[PDB]
Length: 162
Image (cartoon, rainbow, N blue to C red; front, side, top):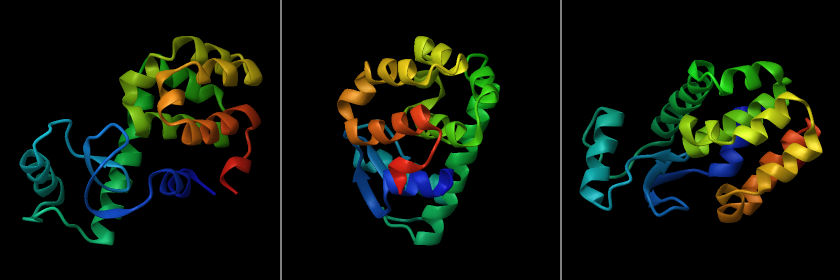
């Protein structure tokens, strides 16, 4: 297991434009295209992202390329954020993956907003952090995924993805 397989499990793979859990146009392995309700706007974002006229359909190779870019972006977002970087640096590799997963799903700004959870994680108060993380719109809207990510923070193992 690793962050790529972890996110493939959580996000799946769809080669045509779909809507994510919030109703936003998305493609591939959880690649958000736009928050606009316009499919045409989403298609324009897709073409720009892939570098060709796609008409809403991509190949697996293309989906994987976007995915690699998006994981990279999540990691750099963490490292450039003054709230996220010290927490990330304090964590072991498995729990670092849990933090990347969160940023992949909700963005740097969103995760950086988990101020109290982040503090508990830096203090290595795992059970307390797990309870605090679940007191969130995140957990209430995507509870099974959030439970997997929280279990990863709580235990420092990949047990929730086996």
